[PDB]
Structures are given as structure tokens and as C-alpha cells.
Image: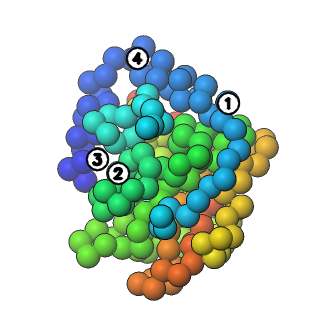
């Protein structure tokens, strides 16, 4: 909020050639990422996403269906999950691209930040935006499933496609299962 304002303000002061080289470095990481075993963030050395870091924030996720703009951070440690959404370890960077699947995790509400509390309100067709460096990527929801903390392939990188999954715990205030809201990239570029 204050954080989101500070983020966009810093980005607008950054050099264009440098904004572009960073983007390309993240795309290079996405093009080479091997499939690995993705663990539940809510249970149990990294240069991961360095090119995207702006005072430790890698951007924010914007979800008009639930009136949220939540800062994103690297990893899903509790330090992070207390203050915003975390990018899941082993998944794509949120810079999109063919054969990518980024995964953004937040608690189902904290006492003073709703975060992903209202994620059950999202429906197929809903559009959310990843704001990353000076870019904004639109994703349109095409699948919503609830799974056991051991059930986790709907976050599989599917060849050809560009996906982003918003991930939280469910039922509300019980948190025994995981709610996955998957969106697929649609054409959108931020206005100038």
C-alpha cells in the first residue's frame, strides 16, 4: 500500500536499458528452469529472482475481484508471509513466457491484512495482474481446485502455456487443504 506506492515510485526512477536487461535475465531463467519437486509452503543460499528485487520486493499482485494489491517477495518463509505474498520455490519467475508456471502464495487472512482471505470469491473469467519491475502481466482464471497438501500437480509447468497460480489454505480459519486459483496469460500491456 505504502509499500506498493514506494515500489512503483522506485521503478519509475530506474534506467530504461537496465529495466530491459533485468527483464531479459528473468526470461533467460524461465527458459532454462528444470522441473523439480514442489513442497507445501505452509509446512516445514538463494540468488533466486535477484534481477527482480527492488528493496526486496519483486512487485505486487493485483486482484480486482477481491479489492487487493499485495506486495510480492521471494520465498514463503514466515517473515515473508506475515507481510505479503511469496513466490514459490522451484517455480517460474512471474515474468511469464511460454512453458512457465509461476506460483504466488499468501495466508488466508491475517488479523490486520486480508491478503488471500477472500480468494474463494474468485471465479473462472476473473482477471488478476502481476506488477513486476515496470511491466504488468494479465492472467485470466481458467481453473480453481482444492487439494490436500500432498496433491500438488495442478502447478505443473504445462508445455506451450503461460500460467500463474494464486495459492492459499482452505477452509477459512481451518487451513487443512490448499486452494489453487490458476489463470492463463492474456494480451495486456501497461499504458505509457
- Label 1 and label 3: CA atoms lie apart by 30 Å
Which mark is nearer the camera, 3 or 2? 2
- Tell me which residue sits at (26%, 76%) in the image: 111
Relative image position of residue 129 (x, y in whole percent): 49, 50
- Tell me which residue sits at (36%, 73%) in the image: 109
- Tell me which residue sits at (54%, 40%) in the image: 93
Q: Nearer the viewer, residue 116 or 33?
A: 33
- Label 3 and label 2: CA atoms lie apart by 7 Å
Q: Quadrant of residue 187?
A: top right
Q: Which residue is mark 4?
A: 18
Which mark is nearer the camera, 4 or 1? 1
Q: In the rendering, which numbered label is found on residue 4?
A: 3
- Counting residues from the N terminus, which is met first, the one under dot 4 or under dot 1? 4
- Label 2 and label 4: CA atoms lie apart by 22 Å
Q: Secondary structure at mark 1?
A: helix
Q: Secondary structure at mark 4?
A: helix
- Label 4 and label 1: CA atoms lie apart by 22 Å
Mark 3–mark 2 contact, CB under 8 Å? yes
Q: In the rendering, which numbered label is found on residue 82?
A: none
Mark 2–mark 1 contact, CB under 8 Å? no
- Counting residues from the N terminus, which is met first, the one under dot 2 or under dot 4? 4
| Snapshot colouring | rainbow
- Label 3 and label 4: CA atoms lie apart by 21 Å
Mark 2–mark 4 contact, CB under 8 Å? no
- From the viewer's perspective, tell me whether residue 16 is left or right of residue 150: left
- Counting residues from the N terminus, which is met first, the one under dot 3 or under dot 2? 3
Q: Which residue is mark 2?
A: 71
Q: In the rendering, which numbered label is found on residue 32?
A: 1
Callout 1 crowding tier (Cα within 10 Å): few <14, some 14–19, many ≥20: few
Callout 4 crowding tier (Cα within 10 Å): few <14, some 14–19, many ≥20: few
Relative image position of residue 76 (x, y in whole percent): 43, 55
Amino acid at each position: 500500500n505504502e509499500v506498493i506506492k514506494e515500489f512503483d515510485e522506485t521503478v519509475s526512477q530506474m534506467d530504461k536499458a537496465e529495466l530491459e536487461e533485468r527483464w531479459r535475465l528473468a526470461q533467460a531463467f524461465n527458459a532454462t528452469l528444470k522441473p523439480s519437486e514442489i513442497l507445501d509452503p505452509f509446512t516445514e543460499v538463494s540468488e533466486y529472482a535477484n534481477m527482480l528485487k527492488v528493496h526486496e520486493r519483486i512487485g505486487y499482485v493485483e486482484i480486482p475481484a477481491i479489492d487487493q494489491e499485495i506486495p510480492m517477495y521471494v520465498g514463503t518463509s514466515e517473515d515473508i508471509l506475515q507481510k505479503g505474498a511469496g513466490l514459490l520455490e522451484g517455480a517460474s519467475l512471474p515474468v511469464g513466457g511460454e512453458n512457465t508456471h509461476t506460483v504466488i502464495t499468501a495466508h488466508r487472512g491475517l488479523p490486520t491484512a486480508e491478503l488471500f482471505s477472500q480468494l474463494d470469491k474468485m471465479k473462472k473469467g476473473d482477471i488478476f495482474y502481476l506488477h513486476v519491475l515496470d511491466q504488468v502481466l494479465a492472467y485470466q482464471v481458467d481453473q480453481i481446485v482444492t487439494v490436500e497438501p500432498n496433491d500438488f500437480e495442478p502447478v505443473l509447468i504445462q508445455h506451450g502455456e503461460d500460467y500463474a497460480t494464486l495459492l492459499t489454505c482452505t477452509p477459512y480459519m481451518i487451513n487443512s487443504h490448499r486452494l489453487l486459483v490458476r489463470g492463463k496469460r492474456i494480451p495486456y500491456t501497461a499504458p505509457i
